[PDB]
Image (tube, rainbow, N blue to C red):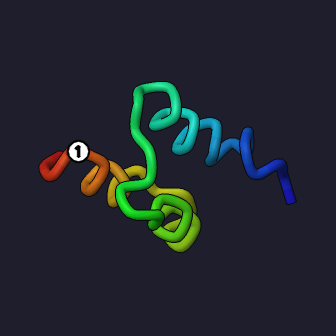
Amino acid sequence: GSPPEADPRLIESLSQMLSMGFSDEGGWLTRLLQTKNYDIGAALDTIQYSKH
């Protein structure tokens, strides 16, 4: 596997929130992301964007 901090999905979906100023809104951030092939769609939903 690729490094869990700069993978095409993590430099996209993790680096987005890390750069913009989001975090774990409870500790689910990793859980949410990984289970949805690194999804910011459902991640952003709880990280202060309750509407896309």
- Using residue 14 as the reference point, say whether residue 43 is left or right of it: left
- Using residue 9 as the reference point, say whether residue 39 is left or right of it: left
- Write down the quadrant of residue 37 in the picture: bottom right
* Mark 1 Cα-neighbour bin, 10 Å: few <14, some 14–19, many ≥20: few
* Quadrant where the image shows the N terminus: bottom right
Q: What amino acid type should be assigned to the residue bearing mark 1?
A: Gln
Front-most of 8 and 19? 19
- Using residue 25 as the reference point, say whether residue 14 is left or right of it: right
Mark 1 highlights which residue? 48
Furthest residue in direction top, as rendered? 19
Residue that appears at 73% across and 39% down = 6
Front-most of 5 and 38? 5
Residue that appears at 52% across and 34% down = 18
| Image coords of residue 33 (percent x, y) | 51, 61
- Write down the quadrant of residue 21 in the picture: top left
| Image coords of residue 25 (percent x, y) | 36, 56
- Write down the quadrant of residue 49 in the picture: top left
